[PDB]
Amino acid sequence: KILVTGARGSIGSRVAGKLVERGLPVRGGVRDLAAPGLPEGVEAVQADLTRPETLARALEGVDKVFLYTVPEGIAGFVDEARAAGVRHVVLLSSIAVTWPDADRDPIGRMHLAVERPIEESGLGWTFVRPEALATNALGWAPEIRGGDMVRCAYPGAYTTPVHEEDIADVVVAALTTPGHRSAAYALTGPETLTQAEQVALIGEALGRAVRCERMPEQEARAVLEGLYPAEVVDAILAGQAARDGRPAEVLDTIRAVTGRPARTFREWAGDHVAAFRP
Ligand SMILES: NC(=O)c1ccc[n+]([C@@H]2O[C@H](COP(=O)([O-])OP(=O)(O)OC[C@H]3O[C@@H](n4cnc5c(N)ncnc54)[C@H](OP(=O)(O)O)[C@@H]3O)[C@@H](O)[C@H]2O)c1
Image: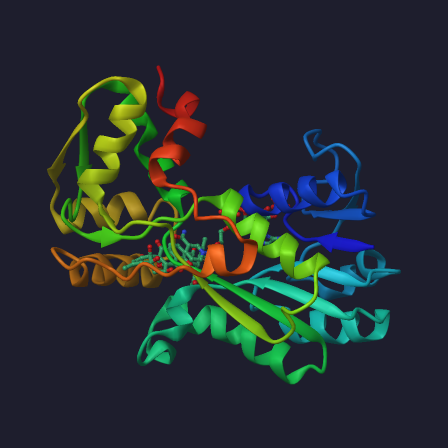
């Protein structure tokens, strides 16, 4: 039996669906229990990782967990997981934990605050550490639905966006096959691309030329603060500024783990084309 925390999430839902396809018993952790929408064959359980007293019920009879990073409550998770007899935890982390002075980066900190307790817990683990999620591009959907111009703080900043389906495939491999215990996988997509190039590729999926223009940092900050705490917005903008005009590393880790090349961002855009069509 596997508990998939965040079974409604972009990554978690695909982990859960893939495990059900394999005939495995899947419990799906949710903060909102009543709403429909979980993948078929997933047993819903209401829990909140910030309320680890909720976790005893969710973990009963569970051998393995797919864990989203929620630092408030990690010590409680570890205690409940140990008490329940969980053998393996696959954590969705971040490549930021691998960067120099990661302790001084809000994003690196948050993810290290979960990795370190798991490493000390005595539980088996696998860490999955993606770079930029291709789904970050969904933030442009209102603009792309509405016309052929998108605003970016750093049109020329490079990332190496990774398809959520690849992340889910790596997680499922770690949950279901040998050789992943104490592994930490830094995942990228197959190509480093600028923000403007990503916008253009979404346009290519739509049959339309979609352009990108710069916006001031203060404007970008206001937009990002709709999604994230100020500390995180500052880290994102600093990271983009550092990648302006500087191609990022492409790693072959997805293929190393799964045997399949990483899915392209262009394929991602085709997969999500409905989000961008008006
Ligand atoms: N954005 C990036 O470029 C980037 C880069 C590297 C790593 N990451 C990592 O990827 C994560 C995003 O994954 P995603 O795209 O799948 O996100 P998502 O679709 O927003 O899903 C996030 C999931 O987290 C669950 N969750 C959050 N707080 C929780 C809590 N207190 N208790 C239980 N579950 C909780 C939510 O559960 P409910 O749906 O039940 O509320 C939700 O299903 C980030 O948070 C970060 O750790 C992101």
